[PDB]
Image 1 (cartoon, rainbow over the protein chains, first blue to last red):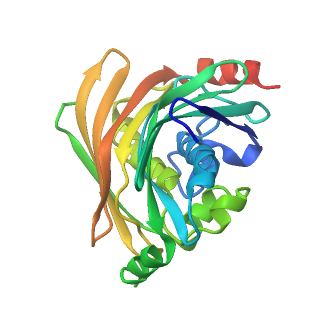
Image 2: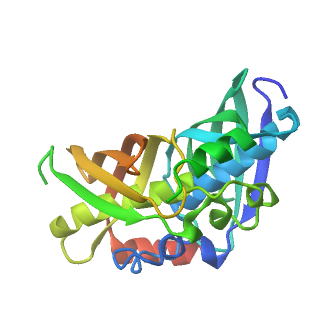
Amino acid sequence: MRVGERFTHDFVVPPHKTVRHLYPESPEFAEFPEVFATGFMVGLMEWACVRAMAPYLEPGEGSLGTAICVTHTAATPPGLTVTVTAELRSVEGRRLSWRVSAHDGVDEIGSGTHERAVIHLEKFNAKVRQKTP
Amino acid sequence: MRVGERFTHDFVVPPHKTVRHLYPESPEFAEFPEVFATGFMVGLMEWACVRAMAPYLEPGEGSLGTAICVTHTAATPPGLTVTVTAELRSVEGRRLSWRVSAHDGVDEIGSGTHERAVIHLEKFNAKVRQKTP
């Protein structure tokens, strides 16, 4: 991969990626319109960047999303295709940053940046076990 | 609403709020350690802000998330209690910005800002239906 390169990730929004599906536990949500949740959009942006950086990982490595900083300016009902465009902003050792944007074929729905960190998966897993009840 | 107003809520992370649950579709995320997804943390942070604003909305009003800008620097397995605090930092027109932070009892897991917009609900819903394939 190269800095300034763009990677695209296409995802048709299904009925189960709406606000109420992010937190079915939430009475305060279950009257939101049936639209693509910001939290799901963040996940889609991470997923796009994960794919983009795959040819960069070595065996035994994964990555974490360590920062997300984006707008969400238009709502997307199920049925539309959301395309995330990830542009590599920098890569240095275990750190990588991306400019991200998303569009649903009708509106640009949001944009900003995302940062990820390469991790040793097994080391990470162990750390998580150290926190597990 | 008064700048400085804070609201806090607690959330025991259940098994179905891990990364693999945000996007089961992702062959990529299926691999992943069983930790609270960034997207779910964002939703919990938005949920805090939604609750904090509710008392001040007139009938027929709702709000939409318009920006999220957070770090997520420590991972959380199911079973831990995540505490989210939201503090109103600014109000301008129909828009409110909150300082948000989350802690799982061991680590501060993320922090940053979230912006929302107060909207006319019905109008918004109609617009969504008009954008629906």
